[PDB]
Amino acid sequence: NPGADPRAAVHMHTFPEIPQSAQYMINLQQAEAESMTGVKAFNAGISG
Amino acid sequence: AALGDTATAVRGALDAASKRELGILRRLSAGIIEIGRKIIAMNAEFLDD
């Protein structure tokens, strides 16, 4: 029907957006643990 | 730290890590040496020619 263009009339929900802070917090915690122990474990990424 | 920007800039990190591991390694080695000395002492007399 007129007055309702599909791009606003229909909507397909998707996953929400993760904010840029959780990534930073995880990286900070992992780096702190690695510094404390002293073994880098070649981790937090590809084992290589 | 510095997981790859210069050949020397990565040598320091592994050096420090190994140097830190060395102390624990030495403590465990001392324990093993003590065990060995006790074993030698027991072999001295309990065992036959």
Image (spheres, coloured by chain):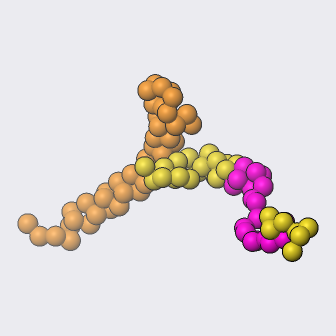
Chain colours: A yellow, B orange
Q: Position of residue B37 (x, y in %)?
A: 31, 57
Q: Which of A12/A43 is in front?
A: A12
In the rendered image, residue B34 lying in the magenta stretch gets the answer no
In the rendered structure, which segment of residues is drawn in magenta? A8-26
Which residue is located at x 46 percent, y 40 percent? Answer: B18
Q: Residue furthest front?
A: A2
Q: Position of residue A5 (x, y in %)?
A: 84, 66
Which residue is located at x 20 percent, y 71 percent? Answer: B46
Q: Which of A25/A9 is in front?
A: A9
B8 on left or right of A17: left
Q: Which image quarter holds the C terminus of chain B?
A: bottom left
* Residue A18 in which image quadrant: bottom right
Q: Residue furthest left?
A: B49
Placement of B45 over or under B28, stated as above or below: below
A40 on left or right of B29: right
Q: Position of residue B34 (x, y in %)?
A: 37, 56
B22 on left or right of B40: right
Placement of A9 over or under B16, stated as above or below: below
